[PDB]
Amino acid sequence: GAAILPDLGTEILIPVCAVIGIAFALFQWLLVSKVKLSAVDHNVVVKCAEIQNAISEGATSFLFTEYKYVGIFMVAFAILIFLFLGSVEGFSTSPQACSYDKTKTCKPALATAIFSTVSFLLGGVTSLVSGFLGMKIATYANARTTLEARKGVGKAFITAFRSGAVMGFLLAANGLLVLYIAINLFKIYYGDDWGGLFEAITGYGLGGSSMALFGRVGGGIYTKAADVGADLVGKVERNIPEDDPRNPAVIADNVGDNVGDIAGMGSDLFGSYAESSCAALVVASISSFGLNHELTAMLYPLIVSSVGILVCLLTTLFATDFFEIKAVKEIEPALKKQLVISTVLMTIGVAVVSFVALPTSFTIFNFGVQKDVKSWQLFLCVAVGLWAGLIIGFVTEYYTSNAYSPVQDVADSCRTGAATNVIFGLALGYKSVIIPIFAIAISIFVSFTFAAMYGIAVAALGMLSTIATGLAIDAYGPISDNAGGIAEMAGMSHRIRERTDALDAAGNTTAAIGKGFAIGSAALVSLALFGAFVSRASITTVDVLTPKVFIGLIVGAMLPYWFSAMTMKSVGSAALKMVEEVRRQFNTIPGLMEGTAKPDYATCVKISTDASIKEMIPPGALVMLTPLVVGILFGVETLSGVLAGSLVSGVQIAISASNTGGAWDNAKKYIEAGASEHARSLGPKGSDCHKAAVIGDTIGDPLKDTSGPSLNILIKLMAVESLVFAPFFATHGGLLFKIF
Amino acid sequence: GAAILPDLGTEILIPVCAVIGIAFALFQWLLVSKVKLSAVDHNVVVKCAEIQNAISEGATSFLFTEYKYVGIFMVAFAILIFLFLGSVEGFSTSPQACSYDKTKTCKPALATAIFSTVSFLLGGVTSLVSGFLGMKIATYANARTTLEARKGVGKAFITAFRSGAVMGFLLAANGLLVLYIAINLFKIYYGDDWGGLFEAITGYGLGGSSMALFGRVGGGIYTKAADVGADLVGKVERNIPEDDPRNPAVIADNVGDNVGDIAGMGSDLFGSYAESSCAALVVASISSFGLNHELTAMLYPLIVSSVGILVCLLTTLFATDFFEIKAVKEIEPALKKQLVISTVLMTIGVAVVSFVALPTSFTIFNFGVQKDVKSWQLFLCVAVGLWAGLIIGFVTEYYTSNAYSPVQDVADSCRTGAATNVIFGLALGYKSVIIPIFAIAISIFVSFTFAAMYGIAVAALGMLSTIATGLAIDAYGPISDNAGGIAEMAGMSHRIRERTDALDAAGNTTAAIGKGFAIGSAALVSLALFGAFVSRASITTVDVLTPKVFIGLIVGAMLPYWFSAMTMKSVGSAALKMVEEVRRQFNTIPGLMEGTAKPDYATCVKISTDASIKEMIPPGALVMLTPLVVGILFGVETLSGVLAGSLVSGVQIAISASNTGGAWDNAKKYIEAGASEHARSLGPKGSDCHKAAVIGDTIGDPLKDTSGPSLNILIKLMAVESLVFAPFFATHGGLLFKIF
Ligand SMILES: CCCCCCCCCCO[C@@H]1O[C@@H](CO)[C@@H](O[C@@H]2O[C@@H](CO)[C@@H](O)[C@@H](O)[C@@H]2O)[C@H](O)[C@H]1O
Ligand SMILES: CCCCCCCCCCO[C@@H]1O[C@H](CO)[C@@H](O[C@@H]2O[C@H](CO)[C@H](O)[C@@H](O)[C@@H]2O)[C@H](O)[C@H]1O
Ligand SMILES: CCCCCCCCCCO[C@@H]1O[C@H](CO)[C@@H](O[C@H]2O[C@@H](CO)[C@@H](O)[C@H](O)[C@@H]2O)[C@H](O)[C@H]1O
Ligand SMILES: CCCCCCCCCCO[C@@H]1O[C@H](CO)[C@@H](O[C@H]2O[C@@H](CO)[C@@H](O)[C@H](O)[C@@H]2O)[C@H](O)[C@H]1O
Ligand SMILES: CCCCCCCCCCO[C@@H]1O[C@H](CO)[C@@H](O[C@H]2O[C@@H](CO)[C@@H](O)[C@H](O)[C@@H]2O)[C@H](O)[C@H]1O
Ligand SMILES: CCCCCCCCCCO[C@@H]1O[C@H](CO)[C@H](O[C@@H]2O[C@@H](CO)[C@@H](O)[C@@H](O)[C@@H]2O)[C@H](O)[C@H]1O
Ligand SMILES: CCCCCCCCCCO[C@H]1O[C@@H](CO)[C@@H](O[C@@H]2O[C@@H](CO)[C@@H](O)[C@H](O)[C@@H]2O)[C@H](O)[C@H]1O
Ligand SMILES: [K+]
Ligand SMILES: [K+]
Ligand SMILES: [Mg+2]
Ligand SMILES: [Mg+2]
Ligand SMILES: [Mg+2]
Ligand SMILES: [Mg+2]
Ligand SMILES: [Mg+2]
Ligand SMILES: [Mg+2]
Ligand SMILES: [Mg+2]
Ligand SMILES: [Mg+2]
Ligand SMILES: [Mg+2]
Ligand SMILES: [Mg+2]
């Protein structure tokens, strides 16, 4: 009937867990504030701090500019939501029959047009705040982990990891607390209409990912224009070290890590968290939980996320307190232990939550029919996504860490030049999709079979249930990356850079793992939302063999390529400009190459700024307008096909791009470290094998930091966007077919 | 109702047009034989003959080796077809009610098993003959083109182009004649059972493309191992000309153009032709034409291809006798006009065919129901295919020719090194898919809407109705390529090479165009075959939102990545071996770098022979086993998703890979030619820009010549295979769902 945990217990447990997470983030920041520096050894400390500030200012300054354009576009788009959703019942103010049950009376559509607009703006704001907080902690932790590197890898690891945990706990706890509050606020207006309530709440996911789209693309173009320009002139052309202060692009580069890899990705992951919770809420709201107004069972997804914060806090302790890194080969294994521990504990967590927060039987909406489901089946839906995630992590590690043969062979292929390096790296990323796809399909089959779109949605959330940790291991990498850049720029000892290099290479693997979790969960939520879209738009069958569905399927499968085209070329063009800028400085400013004059950092910052702010617009436009263009002109059947093809096609290029790029970076890192004889035989730095590895690395740079990771957003965003506009498309869409 | 053209009329016309095409081919071969050479200056002549022989022997010898393996694979698979099909009705010899008309009696399913094996074997034999005859004309024409280049570019054009026409007309005529014969012979047995007759005839395409898959993959690995090795060591490492006779890999490189770009391609296109005709014939056989035994209308696709041959003969005369080339900038436009003229004349021919060979009204089988279709709508189905082809040609030219800005900016990006060449070449490929996809989507919509799977099929066929000319402009390219390999190897003057380079650049564009036609028609026929499969397998609805279909969709979308991983890895590995060997000869054979010692060519030929014969197998296994493993294990609904997914997904990567490869080749060719201030400034040969262009080109080599082009075969071959095995999967498959 109803569950062991009462509605009130749930109303308390969720925000408590949120505050536990925020508290624990604040505590970790406090620990990290113990490492001291300012700009007012000791000369070294002053240099770190001066470098931290330059970076800190650059990141702040670009986010402010980027957030200004995105906030304006957000406001415009919120108006389209209001207008389009408001037009379904001609802006009437009267109630009408429930979309989900014509025998009942529901709040007016116009109202849901307003609360959708509201949840949208909430999600956009929470997304910018996610990116921004992430950027604040990263640009605060970077120099601190550099200084801690003076004491050994282990101490630097620890401060990079605590700081990632600050980012992970703040975003997980925050995205959860804001949703919970918005649900409770909305419920005041909605009453017994839970359908209209969680329909309205859907705009939150749409707000998260809409903003994430620009954050990832804008940041991604800023950082990679710099990265490529810096590394090419400096390492390939001039034979100076990576991240050398004579290099005019290096500040842009390191600012880059913070505005892309940190702020773009914090947004992106908030988008994933939000869409997944929303997808689950929407199907539950017209299932037994929502129809019977059972609030615990209804908020099962938030209860899972709540218990996930607890599990991740416990998990974090293993890497920060219970264990110490003494040898570099211990870094990658430690990060991985974080995944294994959280997954195991979280399986326990989800079982307890399922025992306590669900009745043993209930029904789940299934394309018009109430399907009988058991709490043990729903446990299995969350679990399969949770384990699918771990699988994806293990395979990604295998294909991107330089501790294994796929990356070692890519490095090796450098002996025959850049061409063979690239060909091997491309083959590696292609090859890498196989198992993650099987994992995704298995977890689709199981969750779909057990609980239809609800099953699939909470399998997406299961995959993201350990997101505080996931964000911790990922945020850890750009912090480490900056740390080594500050070392080189501070003039510090050769062996400080060796330590940070080793943290950094582990970070490379870890970034590829986050992209995997983001692609796996995007595939799952997007499928759940596609199905919810189909119901909400009153389509009886999405029949692949009809002209409308098929042209949607093939065109939708083209979109990820069109998107990749724009974003690769933006980076290509901007990087070309950056190389010319860097060259100009080295060739023209007397004493630059000799270390006696200062480079002009601001000109490189500007090339990145201009290119990104300008070139983020078409890809953003492509993704946000496609559902509106196709929904209005062609209709819901054709958009159905678009969503299916973009999902299935988009994930392939997304996985292969990220793993290719990750593999070229770590192959280059392998040569740079010379930690085995095979690795030493490709060296030293500046060797022909090394330069071939650098060429691969910088082709990989836009693949994995601009186009690849954003593709997961192209897919999940079109999908929520379609669902939110479903009533409008069902009613007023399909124009070309109405006319002729 | 009868057409204006009687049945007997049709029976005469088709073989007559076949013969006319064979005669035209022979006449052209004869004209080309007027160019004299023998191995028994006049020193240039002797030398060209010797080299011509070394290529010819290497090409004959590789194909005999490949074709042996492939022929053994073919007999084995033929047994499998017989057993699997024969097992559906437990090998019974009794007649059964016709599934298309329960009042009639039809031939035993065992008969259809037997005849499917027979058509398969014809198709395989014809595909190997197609490739072999292609290689024989190319390895005859190549040196004759070198010699004619002594008189000028236009003379060398005429010889290469007459020689492509040899291949085009032989392949188109012979494929048409064999189909026509097989239909008449099977009819002797089937009599009035046209359903059985044409169900059995479908083996022909399956044998066509099974043989092609190995030919393309085998030939492709062979050629690119050689090419990457020769080019990287000779041009990038040792600063010697391309095709320098000092390079041990150059014989293997030039044999490679004949064994991949010619023999692999010829078989590939033959399978396109065979599948498209077969798909139109299966649907018509249970539509009014087949149910009413109306021979002319039944053979409408063959009549279309017969008229296509006449149209192409006419079109060929424009490039062969009526215009002459006197300047390098006229080569590409002459080649473009061949497609414009054939398209414009075939529009008229197809209008005529549609007027005389169809009743004005009839019905087409459509998912169990006879749909009313008029002959003018059928005209449009064929015509949208034809016109979508030309759109694809124009767009592909725009993206791959160095007369235009996309490639010139790709060459331009060399100014900043190999990493920017590759980022730009990658973005260009991705970008290039937009319009071809839109054209394919429009042809699907039009032909689907008018005439279901039949209209789609004859749309595939319409795109291929000008195949004799399509093959001629394509085959023209490798012949031209060899021509310049032979020029350099014969130590001919720089002027001869400049001419061949102009011919060869245009061949690069024309190869990309051919690939665009192969991919276009593959998408179309695969959709037609996918729909026909669904009927044969008794599926009521392929519904995307079912666990079975959806897991097939996403796994299907992954197959083209797994295939690309294997083929790219193979070329990479064989290339790496090739570089090692070339390096060793330059570094240890005293006098080789100075021209006083002969290299060892055979070793390079060996490395590429062993690699290709061994590595062709797994990718061939993956394509041919997937329908069997999926149909038997998961069943016909899952296989449906696999077909839809592989089609929509594989078409994106196939187009981008090919156009990217083509763009890198021509960006390089543009630095090589220095025909304008911008081009000159990237040179000269041996410059860092030039070497960056070479790096991009060699990375493009496996993309465009091994994995990219074979991908159309993956798609179209899984589709005809699933159809042939449909009755078997429908009865004995879905094991995993039966046991649980
Ligand atoms: C619908 C659900 C179906 C359930 C069953 C699916 C699970 C089976 C996985 C098959 O995939 C394989 O995975 C890799 C294993 O990691 C590859 O091996 C490879 O083996 C090595 C051999 O040295 C290396 O070459 C590596 O690249 C690579 O791991 C292998 O090619 C690939 O096909
Ligand atoms: C559905 C698709 C069909 C799947 C069925 C698989 C059939 C297995 C065939 C076994 O024979 C193959 O052939 C070559 C020799 O027999 C081997 O390498 C070869 O080994 C020899 C050299 O010793 C050759 O002469 C070389 O050309 C070549 O590289 C190759 O590894 C081996 O696999
Ligand atoms: C059915 C689905 C339909 C959904 C419709 C979606 C509309 C999305 C608009 C995308 O258009 C892009 O924008 C740039 C125009 O701003 C183009 O030119 C260029 O723009 C330049 C900036 O002026 C440069 O950045 C580039 O080199 C680029 O080539 C680029 O070609 C084009 O693709
Ligand atoms: C050989 C390897 C092929 C691999 C395929 C594996 C699948 C196994 C399917 C076997 O099919 C059955 O075989 C019997 C015959 O062997 C049939 O009996 C039928 O056979 C007839 C005699 O031929 C009659 O006596 C009866 O109608 C009788 O029901 C029966 O219908 C049929 O379904
Ligand atoms: C899906 C249905 C959509 C229908 C759209 C129609 C598709 C056809 C697009 C083909 O692309 C065009 O081709 C021209 C070549 O024919 C180029 O012109 C070029 O023509 C040359 C020579 O005639 C040059 O001199 C010029 O630079 C000139 O830009 C042109 O730029 C290019 O974009
Ligand atoms: C969805 C249904 C699918 C069912 C059909 C699947 C059957 C065909 C897959 C064949 O397996 C492949 O085998 C190769 C070799 O056997 C490769 O591994 C290889 O392993 C080594 C040994 O051969 C080397 O060749 C390596 O370079 C290479 O990675 C390759 O990656 C692997 O995938
Ligand atoms: C309660 C929250 C759960 C979280 C705890 C985690 C452990 C449970 C997962 C294992 O799944 C099992 O559950 C049983 C059920 O408990 C089984 O039989 C079930 O048992 C009966 C009802 O409980 C039957 O009527 C059904 O048909 C059904 O097959 C089912 O086969 C089995 O694989
Ligand atoms: K990183
Ligand atoms: K060519
Ligand atoms: Mg870098
Ligand atoms: Mg970085
Ligand atoms: Mg860095
Ligand atoms: Mg990195
Ligand atoms: Mg980088
Ligand atoms: Mg070459
Ligand atoms: Mg060649
Ligand atoms: Mg050549
Ligand atoms: Mg070429
Ligand atoms: Mg080449």
Image (cartoon, coloured by chain):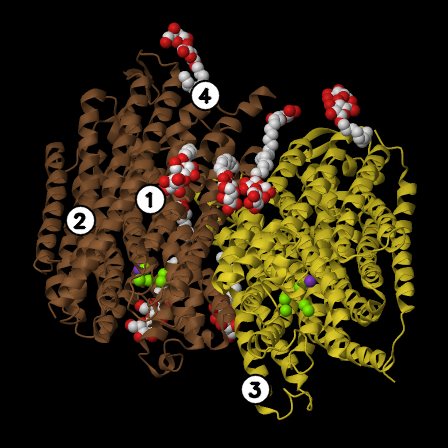
Chain colours: A yellow, B brown
Residue B660 in view of the camera: no
Q: What residue type is labelled 3?
A: Arg
Where is residue B657? Give x, y as percent: 43, 56
**Which of labels 3 and 2 is toward the front?**
3
Name the residue that disc number 4 marks. Answer: B731
**Which of labels 1 and 2 is toward the front?**
1
Label 4–label 3 contact, CB within 8 A:
no
The N terminus of chain A is located in which quarter? top right
Vertical arrangement, residue A369 with respect to residue B390, above or below: above
- Write down the chain letter for disc 3: A
Q: Which of marks 1 and 2 is nearer the N terminus?
A: 2
- The label on residue B82 is none
Q: What residue type is labelled 1?
A: Gly
Residue ID at (47%, 74%)? B413
Residue A304 in view of the camera: yes
**Which of labels 4 and 3 is toward the front?**
3
Most extreme residue toward the front, as rendered?
A: B590
Between the residue at mark 3 and the residue at mark 2, the CA separation in whole angstroms equals: 57 Å
Where is residue A593? Give x, y as percent: 63, 86
Between the residue at mark 4 and the residue at mark 2, the CA separation in whole angstroms equals: 42 Å
- The label on residue B169 is 2
Most extreme residue toward the bottom, as rendered?
A: A590
Q: Is residue B615 left or right of residue B342?
A: right
Label 4–label 2 contact, CB within 8 A:
no
Between the residue at mark 1 and the residue at mark 2, the CA separation in whole angstroms equals: 20 Å
- Write down the chain letter for disc 1: B
Name the residue that disc number 1 marks. Answer: B215
Q: Is mark 4 on a helix, strand or loop?
A: helix
Residue at disc 2, CB closer than 8 Å to ligand 9: no
- The label on residue A584 is 3
Q: What residue type is labelled 2?
A: Phe
